[PDB]
Length: 275
Ligand SMILES: CCCC(=O)N[C@@H](CCO)C(=O)O
Image (tube, rainbow, N blue to C red; front, side):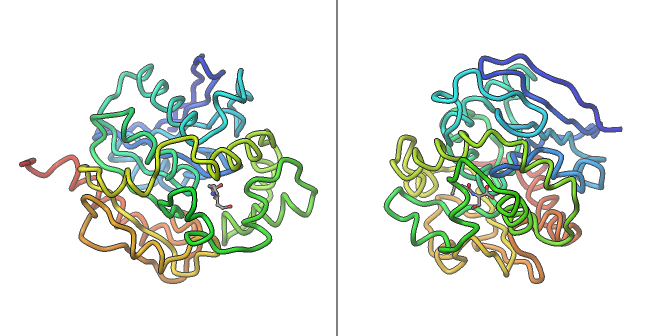
């Protein structure tokens, strides 16, 4: 059973899905124009059966309302504020965080806001300073849509297919079509302007374990760039790459992805801790 409920937050009404796992909590943060529903394989599978998986919808996304104040909410740092508020309301201070793409950038901005975070895993996310956006991401037509407010029908399909990978289904179009397009435009502009904390410096200086897991056929992220990013505490000492997966290995290759995620959660929550 996945438990669905809604929170009244300062950002708006936020939808939250939780598994019934008895173990340590995992906050999973979805990507641009997606929804926590995308994490069905984890919510409903072995990960969610053991651990308390929490998969909200960002303001403007999924089953959440649009933001009360788009100018406050629709940015990497604004979303980080919102997720921190969600975790406050849920009464959970020590989650492991998994962030997918935009969600990974949000997770990076959460490091300063959510001090008892036990670890952060980022997938589809190159930590970049504002001037490095061109280096960390692959230029292309779908990448261009990340910051585009108005999507045509073909835009919705192209973006959904490229972000979610195989297998595709119609429900994904519904998720992407719902997204408040203002959120795309404002977030991307603010990202390029560096309105939040410099993510390159944040990950270099962060002491908590940071895990990096990507699909080899990533269409958005430059894996060469990612493999050169300095992390304060890179989990297992390297960035990880999964064959036969692209931007969304958690759904494209769930068993292989789950091996990494489960091991990371175990390492961050059930190993003896020494400074
Ligand atoms: C570029 C800002 C972060 C972002 O929107 N990432 C996208 C991938 C690129 O289209 C995502 O969240 O999937």
